[PDB]
Image (tube, coloured by chain):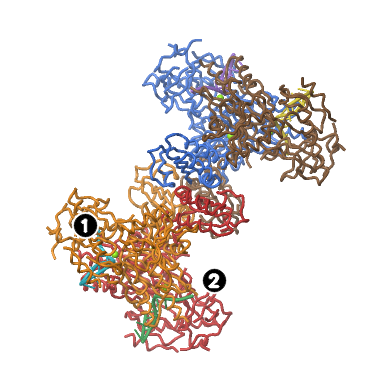
Chain colours: A red, B orange, C blue, D brown, E yellow, F cyan, G purple, H green
RNA sequence: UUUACAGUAU
RNA sequence: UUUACAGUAU
RNA sequence: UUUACAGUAU
RNA sequence: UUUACAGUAU
């Protein structure tokens, strides 16, 4: 029955566990955004940067891996439709910010347009081209009055001009202090570290509609206060209240299950059905099942599914392409209701999203900007049994596979023996079910020994086949082979 | 450099392994379709069928699980835009064929329109509505001449009218024999079993362009011959030749690697880049990476990628929705080249496909009809570490997770102890890194014992938390707990 | 340099661990006897006893297992060189004490001569035949003065006659209370439970030379006091002192290593060499090695070895036969020095010992009475790898063994298959090194399948061979066999 | 019912398995001696030997380990009651034979008295002091007639003087060839390798009472013949017969179970009871249990037990001291019957034995000369769970043990953390049952972290405790510790 | 294997 | 496999 | 623990 | 976060 406005919106900060600081936005008991931080974020850090290798170009900002820099992102003041081999010389030093953190193998997006975020404004020092209103918001007037050689945040709504000036200045101080520690050293160095998860919250998530800001630990709270004030949000001060229940905070507000759902592949919807979220090389793919009038059911579920998808998108910090497979509905009107629901349900999201109509296949494609790395990238690792595939090849299939591999290697001229080192049950199978087979191979391709040793240090999909050439063979024992061959 | 026509197209039948009979269509050494059969296929089997429960309706054709029957698929002669609660009464007997085998939880598609496949025709006894030309093909004339109260196959091209009559008859005999063993027994029984993999090949894949039909085993070959003749394909007889190389057949024709590619998640393309195939609840998703002029590269790779996708679609018997993420190309002309390539490259496919333009997201959606079950369904099983997800949740994350679960259970009124039974390293972590935590819980929620026993019979994601109520507790030993609790 | 008398003898009671109460007699820092008790001793308990089955006779004193009763141990008053089939009728009730606890399979020694231990006397109510002096000790006179229709303890030395009377009485009270709860119920019941480890100490180990009695816990201490007083040892009261060091008691007195030595197979001697204690079905066997004048060395070491053996005998509570293999010495005089040393070194032992001369083989046999069960019986369990033997049969030996077993079973008429289920490396070996072998068997003894499945749930010595008769065979998978056969 | 003489005595040679050549002496179907050889024996090999270090003295005869040489065993001709520092100078070369192979840590007995074994004589070239009759046997006369500057075997009984001369010569040839390849090279070299297991048999075990010599393989048989002839035993030739049953040789003669008994700890006796053989640092110890007139039973069993012990002594090649614990018998006459039985039953044994009367403890000590290494030394290895002890310390005991160790290490000044790395269930126990304990330690001995990580790469008795000093600590994870510490 | 050697010592 | 069918629904 | 008991026997 | 940016490229 969720209607925005009915209940309070609190920001719950849970800081009783050293190893995972947690910030929830909750509306009533509905978790609608989560942020965790563990002893950490590198986005928005600024660096003195030396160009590595134009081939836009790559960079050494000090990290184990160089960063990526787009021609689009080079500056006017840093430029001594042209080719980059023109504006920037190798080894050339330049001020650099991180737009996108390191994902998989990519370095990072860096930009020489540098942006500075405060409570109410965002200085764009390195560019006048971009600046103006929060597409979300008397201020066009208050804006002009300001000095400069920038943008106003969704949070200036309830404030005057001095405050913007108060902000605008502090920003500048930074900018100055910024290009000063830049004119004062070698090139490959960190200049500015982004604020931590609590600051960021206070800076970026404090709409006027945030009722309270609860906190489960005193030390932090205190830290919290100083953070507000220093942050120019004096008003909120009264709002920060220390929680002291025996029952844990996120638990009292009944949001831990919801936090967990961020981690499941399936997520149950209100009326019963569910969504399954599956990630893949290319894209994330969400699918949708009904629970128990048909046409109705399909509609209603898809509607729930939209709302949920919208928040899962956020909790799991999901970025890039996303392909949703809504239940199929005949009435075109339904198809629009549903896309609309979706658009509606993602309006609060801070990330740029782009949605799109249900295809004739019943698929809906969308895209959501990478704000930060996702759950799965940052709190999961690739299942090391299957190596991402989520399946394991049945035993025979694999065995017969291996058998063939064995004969092939047996065929090569100059072969003395072949050692197949393999999961136990494979060995069982090759050495019973397929005994004759292996025999045949051995009688046929002649004086070639086929060793197939079982090995409990292996599970099925993994195995090795080695080929031992006439000459190189030893008097080793079958079961001693795995260790002998441990260097491979 | 593959140009259709250059080289011979042989059908390689590999039957030297009892447990996996293998039929390859190869063009030169290019594998372009594979069929494996293991001591098996249920599609096209016919049954006497008793209606279970109208709610189209479900069926008992004898299998552990009832089958699905669409109103669309009920007959005129079996009907004693209306509702099914009208045409078919519960328990009612009716002739039934399988359109689609059992997938996951679904029963099967059954149809009371029954189709009978021979070399040149397909009798549609139970319906005159559908019949006519192979959209792939003097015969419109040869067709009419026939008796009846049906369709002509892509293979009638090189034959006369008597042969169609010769076929047409044999079909009818069957039809008769069909509804006779149907009028002669109870209802829940198998009537017709589909032919095996070799017959099916000969029946369905012998275009005039098939040069030879090689075979690696004598017994089968002989069987093969009788299969041709009985199949009314006398011409091919001369074409069936027994292979006798020491080197295995599929190996001599260098197609085993290609057969294997059907099983990898990544598949390298000619010029270097690759495609990654990822399956998911909803759909399969193929992604495409370049290897090393940009615009060129992207184009050329996407082109290779199309060809490959087309054959992988076939080797892996992939069905349903498929979403391809081609490398992104600016020139719209390229986007059409690529979709076209794809269409071209899938023309030979026997399954109905539907393709579609590259979306503004760079995605291409397509659909390919389920002919049979896919590799992954039929020769893989769900990785039992991760349970499909392809990831495992990092240790702390999981632990902290468990910790919270523990406190929560500790809170419930009437609790005496809580036993967390968990992977070893979780236990390590909860009992060192998080010792104080667990302590706190215990001192706080009072005289409540928190047992956290490590267990080597578990890997990380799996765990148990049990709650032992005041009264129900025992004097068991920490490490004895897992077994005590083995009934859960 | 240990001379008895030099340093204090304290009794250290260590009771800071709920699960193991520990009482050490230490002389200086030399541990010279240890007693542990864990939440326990059954010796000296008294029972109402019903005769089970004359065949002396067995008994039901209530325990899961009946007890053993010697004709020698039946009474005059309980007797309604004769045969027991005479004195005691089946089911006959009689008062019963435990002389020896349950060892391995034996029930227990029970006696109808019942003995009652107090600080200074031992009432022998059920017999006047035995009574008199502690062979270890004015009292022959003090003894007579007493009433009666009994023995004086080694501890009466420093006391008068009233105290013996004070003791003598309390004893009698018990005796009376004893045969009263005996005349007041069915037969199969416990009558008297022996005191706990602390009481027993105070009762049985408090010679006048015990300086202090330290204790590491207050609650127990207090309990301790009441135990002394109730025990009629008022004098010692001043002697009981509570220990309060941060450093653990047994640790401060540097005796924990020595306590541990009770648990090693090897035990280093002062001058360097060592003794190895090995227990066996029959007897314990101690062996003795020198460390680095020969004749000297041998002598001196054997001498150390004697002292040590004497205390190990005690710490490990070793009973029954013991065979020591001293280093060999030519000079007969040495052989006597050494036996004597031994006799000397075991004089303090409370158990009856019998020693004996070094045999011509250099062996010394001795015997030491079972006071209680030994370390190894009470804090060890039979190594479950080797099953007592302390060796594992090398792999080939075992394999070849199994191979032969396999052929044999293959030979039996009416055999269809033989399944060898075996440790992995055995399987490796049988299925590579011995492949031809297994082959031969199979080609020879005909159409008989030899399945040899590796199994990681087994280590080498354990294995199974099953024989599957014509008829009883299944289509199971090689590696599925272990589970199929798990009922055996 | 075994009476020597009733049945044939055959020598069964089983040589159908490359990896274990087997020679059985069987009387009827009673195995009464076994010899196995695997692709091997070093006793009786001769070497050129360089003295390493007088301290008799040690030697380098080429083996990884030097050999032991007794003053008693130096020669007259090699001597340039005195001290060895006199007769033999360091580095001095001398002819050397192996009396006793390498056992455990000992090198080997070597002797400069060299003995040469043929069918009928034994040349003692390097000494005239020793020579004469087989204490087991017209020949005193035949002996004298011989030339020389030696002993007659138990096998000369049925032969003349020429044969002794024929032998005597061949021996000499060897002797000459011996000291020639000795005068013709450096010092550290092998001179003579002892014959293999089949030769040795034929040479040493062919009494006239050996009926047949069966053989299960043709190639070997043939080899066998040439071995006889070359061995001067022409008579036996007719006796060597090739076995050709499908049923394996040792199996047909029903002796495989008996061969196996050589490997069990328990061995059932005819009438039911059994003997348990237990080996130990010092000595082997045999114990004896009855099965179901008492006095009778005890006697009869002990008698069986004697016979069995006698043959087990042989099958298991048992050497050194042996202590038998016969069932106890009152009648002294019985005690002599039994010792006598034993003496009788070991008369055939080739090794020197010395027996002795039953002690007052009921123990019988005996000694049997090491002919070769024993089963357990040569086909077993030390159980690696328990490390010889045959027991494992119960869990708590071990844990509490570890706990104490932990506190102790916590106490040392300059300690930052202590890591206990331990079998899983220990960790369970220390971290539940003993949680407070570990807590206490930590609160008490202050800011000292006690890490106790469970580890599945360990079983209970093994564990590690490390102490990490202020300074040397890291930010490693609890469960990452075992690997971090894997270098220890 | 013979007034011996067997145990035993490295 | 033919104004079809392919996806889709259990 | 005392002309004893200790080993030993189930 | 403002005719933008979001996807996308390493
Ligand atoms: Mg769906
Ligand atoms: Mg996946
Ligand atoms: Mg891509
Ligand atoms: Mg010794
Ligand atoms: Mg042992
Ligand atoms: Mg015994
Ligand atoms: Zn997985
Ligand atoms: Zn063991």
Question: Image point 54% across, 47% down: which residue?
Answer: C432
Asked if one can make out residue C152 in the rendered structure from this viewpoint, the answer is: no
- Residue behind label 2 places its C-beta within 8 angstroms of ligand 3: no
Q: Nearer the viewer, residue D190 or D468?
A: D190
Quick one: which residue is furthest to the right in this view? D80
Residue C30 placement (x, y as % from top left): 64, 36
Front tag of 2 and 1: 1
Disc 1, SS: helix
Q: Relative to residue D98, is residue D479 depicted above or below? A: below
Image mark count:
2
Residue C377 placement (x, y as % from top left): 53, 33
Question: Image point 26% across, 64% down: which residue?
Answer: B163
**Pointer 2 indicates a residue of which chain?**
A
Asked if one can make out residue C157 in the rendered structure from this viewpoint, the answer is: yes
Residue at the disc numbered 2: A64
Question: Ligand 8 quadrant?
Answer: top right
Residue D252 placement (x, y as % from top left): 53, 31
Label 1 crowd bin: few (<14), some (14–19), many (20+), radius 10 Å: some
Disc 2, SS: loop
Q: Nearer the viewer, residue C310 or C45?
A: C310
Of the 4 image quadrants, the one containing the N terminus of chain D is top right
Horizontally, is D39 left or right of A395 in the view? right
**Could you say which disc has been placed on residue D183 in the image?**
none
CA distance for labels 2 and 1: 73 Å
Label 2 crowd bin: few (<14), some (14–19), many (20+), radius 10 Å: few
Residue C329 placement (x, y as % from top left): 74, 29
Question: Image point 38% across, 38% down: which residue?
Answer: C472
Residue at the disc numbered 1: B175
């Amino acid at each position: 029955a969720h209607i925005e406005g009915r209940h309070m919106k609190r920001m719950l900060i849970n800081a009783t566990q050293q190893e995972e600081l947690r910030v929830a936005l909750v509306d009533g008991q509905r978790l609608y955004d989560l942020d965790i931080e563990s002893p950490e974020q590198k986005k928005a850090n600024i660096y003195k940067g030396k160009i590595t290798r134009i081939e836009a170009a790559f960079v050494d900002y000090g990290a184990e891996r160089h960063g990526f820099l787009p021609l689009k992102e080079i500056a006017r003041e840093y430029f001594p439709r042209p080719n980059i081999k023109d504006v920037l010389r190798e080894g050339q030093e330049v001020i650099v910010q991180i737009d996108k953190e390191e994902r998989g193998n990519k370095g990072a997006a860096l930009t020489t347009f540098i942006s500075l975020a405060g409570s109410y404004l965002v200085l764009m020092p390195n560019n006048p081209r971009a600046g103006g209103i929060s597409r979300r918001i008397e201020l066009k007037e208050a804006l002009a009055s300001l000095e400069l050689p920038l943008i106003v945040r969704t949070a200036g709504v309830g404030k005057s001009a001095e405050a913007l000036q108060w902000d605008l200045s502090f920003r500048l101080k930074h900018w100055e202090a910024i290009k000063k520690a830049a004119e004062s050293r070698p090139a490959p160095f960190l200049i500015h570290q982004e604020s931590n998860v609590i600051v960021r919250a206070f800076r970026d998530y404090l709409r006027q509609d945030i009722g309270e800001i609860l906190i489960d630990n005193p030390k932090v709270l205190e830290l919290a206060r100083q953070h507000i004030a220093a942050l120019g949000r004096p008003d909120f001060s009264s709002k920060i209240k220390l929680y002291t229940g025996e029952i844990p905070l996120f638990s009292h507000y009944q949001i831990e299950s919801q936090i967990e759902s961020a981690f499941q592949r399936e997520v149950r919807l209100p009326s019963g059905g569910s969504i399954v979220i599956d990630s893949t090389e290319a894209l994330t793919a969400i699918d949708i099942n009904s629970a128990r009038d048909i046409e109705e059911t399909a509609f209603n579920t898809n509607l729930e599914a939209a709302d949920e998808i919208a928040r899962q998108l956020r909790l799991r910090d999901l970025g890039g392409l996303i392909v949703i497979d809504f239940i199929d509905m005949t009435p075109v009107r339904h198809q629009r209701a549903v896309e609309n629901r979706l658009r509606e349900a993602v309006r609060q999201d801070r990330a740029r999203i782009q949605i799109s109509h249900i295809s004739r296949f019943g698929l809906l494609e969308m895209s959501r900007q990478r704000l930060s790395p996702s759950l799965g990238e940052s709190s999961h690792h690739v299942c090391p049994r299957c190596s991402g595939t989520g399946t394991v090849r049945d035993n025979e299939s694999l065995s017969l596979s291996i058998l063939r591999l064995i004969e092939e290697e047996a065929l090569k001229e100059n072969t003395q023996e072949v050692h197949a080192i393999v999961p136990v049950p494979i060995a069982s199978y090759l050495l019973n079910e397929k005994r004759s087979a292996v025999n045949a191979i051995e009688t046929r391709q002649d004086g070639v020994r086929c060793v197939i040793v079982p090995n409990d240090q292996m599970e099925t999909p993994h195995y090795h086949v080695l080929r031992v050439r006439k000459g190189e063979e030893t008097p080793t024992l079958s079961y001693m082979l795995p260790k002998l061959h441990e260097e491979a």
